[PDB]
Image (tube, rainbow over all chains, first blue to last red; front, top):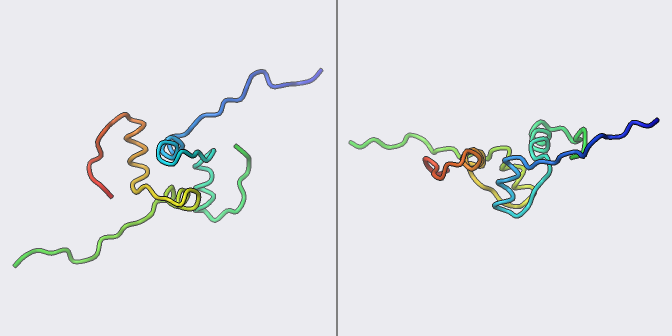
Length: 49
Length: 49
């Protein structure tokens, strides 16, 4: 008996994503995690989008 | 006698501007104000950067 995910995982665009998609035709998934790790000086994200 | 500004004004990149400068080679000044107005639905900013 195996435990499997009951439903699909939902990906959502953030407001920062909306701005970059309107202006640059480009989306960086989970923008805020990158910006916080970038200004804090942390070289590694904990997880992938 | 006229009243004149005593010092140069300061223009600062926000951390979102850091992310988009690195990624897209471009900056949208007052990135967060555009973001907040765009999600709120409001068409006019009070002033420019």
